[PDB]
Amino acid sequence: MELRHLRYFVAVVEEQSFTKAADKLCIAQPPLSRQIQNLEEELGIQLLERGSRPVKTTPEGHFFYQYAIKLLSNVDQMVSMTKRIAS
Amino acid sequence: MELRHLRYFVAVVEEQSFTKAADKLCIAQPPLSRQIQNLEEELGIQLLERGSRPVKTTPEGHFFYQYAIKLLSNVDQMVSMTKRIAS
Ligand code: NA
Picture 1 (cartoon, chains in turn red, green):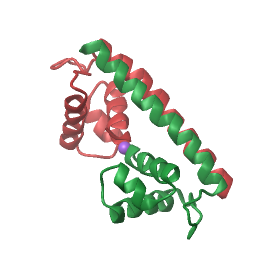
Picture 2 (picture 1 turned 135 degrees about the horizontal axis):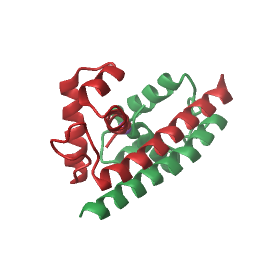
Picture 3 (picture 1 turned 90 degrees about the vertical axis):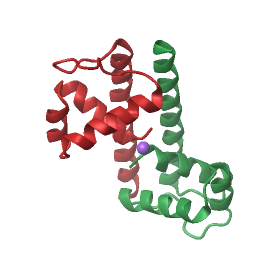
Picture 4 (picture 1 turned 45 degrees about the vertical axis):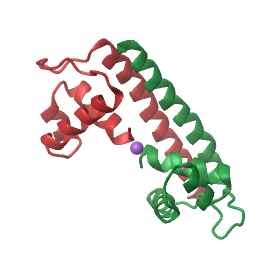
């Protein structure tokens, strides 16, 4: 699992759309969908209700989502601070 | 930046060796070294003292290291708990 998977997943959850998330991340929809599938397959879980319109998380999916946003925020803080040290 | 970069970096810092870190991560040394260089180049900073034997972090490198281990621990906790929900 990579940060890309988390960033893609968060965008899908927030936009409630695979296409709209793809637009926001400046990528095509098909690879985005494949990456989220890859994430679910790696974890051995369903993060999203399959076939849900608009896109809705499963309970474990929403749990994962809430911790994913926390982690991505921490990444941003880490990178920002480390850069500020060197400059 | 991806989780791979953090995992590679942490291993190098802890083993104080590019080769020994590669052994631990079950990969060849050359791609490992390239990935760490890629990480430093992306951030625009030196995480390791260039030419140091044994491998030693820069002050910003050690700072980054300490937050990287925290983040990787959080990733592990997130994945473990989310899996435990679905099972
Ligand atoms: Na990653």
